[PDB]
Amino acid sequence: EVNLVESGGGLVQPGGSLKVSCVTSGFTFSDYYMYWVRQTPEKRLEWVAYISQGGDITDYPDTVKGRFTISRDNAKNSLYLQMSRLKSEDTAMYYCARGLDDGAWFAYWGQGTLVTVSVASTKGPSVFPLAPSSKSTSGGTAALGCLVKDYFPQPVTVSWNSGALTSGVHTFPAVLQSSGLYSLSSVVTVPSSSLGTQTYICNVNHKPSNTKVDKRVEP
Amino acid sequence: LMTQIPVSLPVSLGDQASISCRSSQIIVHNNGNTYLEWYLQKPGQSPQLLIYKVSNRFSGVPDRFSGSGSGTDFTLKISRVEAEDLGVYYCFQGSHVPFTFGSGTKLEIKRTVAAPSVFIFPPSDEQLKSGTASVVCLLNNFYPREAKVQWKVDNALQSGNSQESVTEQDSKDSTYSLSSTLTLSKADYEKHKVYACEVTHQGLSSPVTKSFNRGEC
Ligand SMILES: COC(=O)CCCCCCCCO[C@@H]1O[C@H](CO)[C@@H](O[C@@H]2O[C@H](CO)[C@H](O)[C@H](O)[C@H]2O[C@@H]2O[C@@H](C)[C@@H](O)[C@@H](O)[C@@H]2O)[C@H](O[C@@H]2O[C@@H](C)[C@@H](O)[C@@H](O)[C@@H]2O)[C@H]1NC(C)=O
């Protein structure tokens, strides 16, 4: 099936440079105009650039004109976005998209790759637990989770029983604490009866610091 | 450019909804139709296409969605709002450079009032040893979004060591969840046995409180 995969972003400091890429699958890459779209933290959506099939025709909004450069390698069905002289405002989620011959811009979107632009320092998260000792057992269901404390930059991915616990999962969005550090909780509610047999573990992952932490939560 | 009104849109299931946009200038390309499109960004996902070229439904979009518009005003209409339709809608114009998006209209599903299941999670030793221990209070699956959370350490109103994390609406039942964390240093926390989290909600007549007894082992 058709899909796009962006990759290559992380923490870069102001004035620096980064090159995000996007890999095409499921369609004839060379037949389509490609796009680079971004969404800022305030969820504002902005168009970044486009490039013809040959690679000779491109354009960008003034806001990114001259610092950014879009390119594509038809040979490897990849699309690239060279970013230079990064500004903090450039901090966002970068998506690559494919349109329709018919007259549509973004019919297919990727997953996105988050580019953070600051003078801050990469720090791994401390995966703490939340113990449902007693003041939570309201009967035949209680809540529990792992508090992913102190980390930067975003993002941090959390999973339960490595994907073997979908429904019930409540992973809250990150909050930029005072320390300049993010923190978030991922709670889940489960039948008090499940405890013991149902081994519950949260697998945290903060790629930006190569932190791969697992934590078994229990009664 | 573009202007999208309304910002928020409370709608009941089955209801009809209308979101409109007005481009700064009459939007039309090589007369090759007006290239005005509508996107739906379901929560926690990338945006997706619904209608393009003012009214063409993209493949896979159900007919409850329709588009229209003239000169500078375009409207998206949902005849029967279903649960899956919650998220933020965006209009987009590709007839002129720069290609612009509308600021967005968040569609929230109006549901029957529900009470939050409050919970209190005291700090586990593993963070206590590290020093800073945080007590989290969970207000699970409620509606509306109006919820006040006050911290009562013994009986002190902590007007500082707390933060809030509110989720987006859940398509399974149209509820929200909220988490408030009282972040204390071993000492402050260690100094008091009981910690209370007081919840006040619309479906909550008598503001429920949630407290625990401090301990160690
Ligand atoms: C089903 O099979 C396929 O889809 C296989 C792919 C199609 C076969 C090869 C097609 C070769 C032609 O490719 C088209 O070139 C056009 C330019 O000549 C593109 O249109 C341009 O898109 C730019 C980026 O947004 C910008 O909007 C330009 O203004 C626009 O050109 C304008 O519109 C054209 C349709 C012409 O009328 C031209 O005179 C005019 O200047 C095509 O891009 C598609 O259409 C545009 C409107 C936009 O919706 C893009 O996202 C679409 O992809 C391009 N076709 C493709 C599939 O890329």
Image (spheres, rainbow, N blue to C red):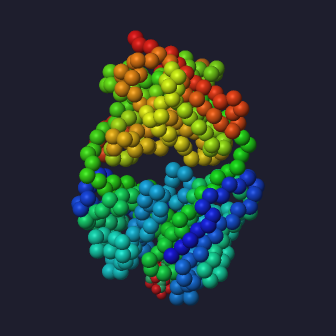
B159 left or right of B70 in image? left
Q: Is residue B35 visible?
A: no
B157 left or right of A52 in image? right
Q: Position of residue B75 (x, y in %)?
A: 66, 71
* Rendered residue at 60%/42% (across/down): B176
Above/below status of B156 relative to A173: above
Nearest the camera: B208 or B94? B208
Q: Position of residue B102 (x, y in %)?
A: 54, 68
Q: Quadrant of residue A202?
A: top left
Above/below status of A98 relative to A168: below
Q: Position of residue B45 (x, y in %)?
A: 51, 53
Nearest the camera: B184 or B3? B184
* Rendered residue at 69%/29% (across/down): B206
Q: Residue furthest top?
A: B217
* Rendered residue at 65%/66% (across/down): B19
Nearest the camera: A114 or B118? B118
Q: Quadrant of residue A175?
A: top left
Q: Is residue A47 visible?
A: yes
Nearest the camera: A185 or B136? B136
Q: Residue furthest left?
A: A16
